[PDB]
Amino acid sequence: SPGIWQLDCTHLEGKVILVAVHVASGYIEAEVIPAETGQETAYFLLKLAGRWPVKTVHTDNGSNFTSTTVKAACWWAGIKQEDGIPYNPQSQGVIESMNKELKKIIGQVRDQAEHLKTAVQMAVFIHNHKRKGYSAGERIVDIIATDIQ
Amino acid sequence: SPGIWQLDCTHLEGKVILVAVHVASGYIEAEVIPAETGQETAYFLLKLAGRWPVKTVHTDNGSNFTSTTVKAACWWAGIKQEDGIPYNPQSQGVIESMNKELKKIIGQVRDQAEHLKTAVQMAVFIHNHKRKGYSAGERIVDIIATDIQ
Ligand SMILES: COc1ccc(CNC(=O)c2ccccc2C[N@@H+](C)Cc2ccc3c(c2C(=O)O)OCO3)cc1
Ligand SMILES: COc1ccc(CNC(=O)c2ccccc2C[N@@H+](C)Cc2ccc3c(c2C(=O)O)OCO3)cc1
């Protein structure tokens, strides 16, 4: 559970926003890409696993689940690739809610930058730092530090 | 000191590798960019601070120290920008050694990908996961969790 992440893809300004959510904490990393391809998703997971102890990724769709490039990156990085089927139905809504909150934040910062990617990183910052009294950034560090010891 | 990071720029294949080192743990994030500009450096720090509690950044040179874009990103992200002057004479050496180690890893994985950026991220992965017996990834999480509590 300290190592379980969910991939999420959303669309804005004709571009794709790829998100990895740390399930237990609600912490996120995100990138803007022109279109979701296996190569991009693979590259994004490699980056993520080099930064956090990623044991399991719940993939966002069947194209990424099938992708030979995505499977190669997961093998390289020691990641168990899983489907993202919400056997828990309170997961579909939780992601939808996160895309909504994310997009709200991006709207709140959008004028602060020309490039969508800049506004997306600002939104990642504001999301991870928001106290709800611990923030996502706090929760992920505590969850994982507890696991290490 | 849980929040202190050092910027480092190194060169390979006619490109720039931008590195942020978490001073206490030796954990790193890195990116490939065409050339170090204030805008790229600013963007890299924004990404970094949204992912980890960055209190202080020791900038890698006087151009980034002066950069009005870099100062604007630091202000936005709550980052104290400082010089990277190695008042401890053993800071020049640690960085030199890290660039050497990094470039060595990149050499050990280089054939595993066409794009330098892919090899750099593999190298980041291998660096952060190496047991030294705790890894850099383990140390940074330990250091910061101890601070949160
Ligand atoms: C990240 O540091 C920041 C430092 C300062 C600001 C303040 N806002 C403005 O000055 C501004 C506002 C609106 C439109 C254009 C601009 C001018 N640009 C240069 C901002 C910028 C810088 C670095 C980047 C960017 C962009 C971008 O516009 O997307 O894209 C990737 O690296 C934002 C971000
Ligand atoms: C991260 O997932 C990986 C999955 C598999 C491999 C195995 N190695 C090869 O198949 C290979 C080896 C040498 C040359 C070209 C290739 C073919 N490409 C498509 C690998 C690749 C994929 C995604 C990317 C890349 C690149 C790249 O070549 O740099 O750049 C940004 O996103 C590496 C990385």
Image (tube, coloured by chain):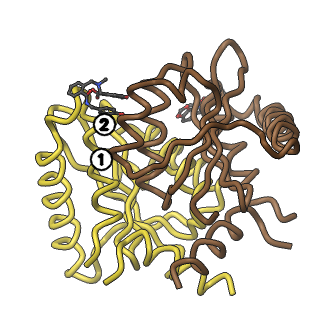
Chain colours: A yellow, B brown
Q: Is residue A108 above or below residue B8?
A: below
Ligand 1 neighbours mark 1 (CB distance < 8 Å): yes
Q: Residues within 10 Å of mark 1 (few under 14, many from 20)?
A: many
Ligand 1 neighbours mark 2 (CB distance < 8 Å): yes
Position in image of residue B130 (x %, y %): 80, 59
Q: SS for tag 1?
A: helix
Q: Nearer the viewer, residue B2 or A125?
A: B2
Three-letter amino acid code at the position of disc 1? Met
Position in image of residue B21 (x %, y %): 67, 48
Q: Circle 2 sits on which residue?
A: A118
Residue appearing at x 48%, y 45% in the figure: A44
Image quadrant containing the N terminus of chain B: bottom right
Residue A19 tag number? none
Residue B97 visible to an observer of this rendering: yes
Residue A122 tag number? 1
Residue appearing at x 51%, y 48% in the figure: A70
Residue appearing at x 16%, y 64% in the figure: A96
Task: Say left or right for A100 vs B27.
Answer: left
Task: Say left or right for A57 vs A13.
Answer: right
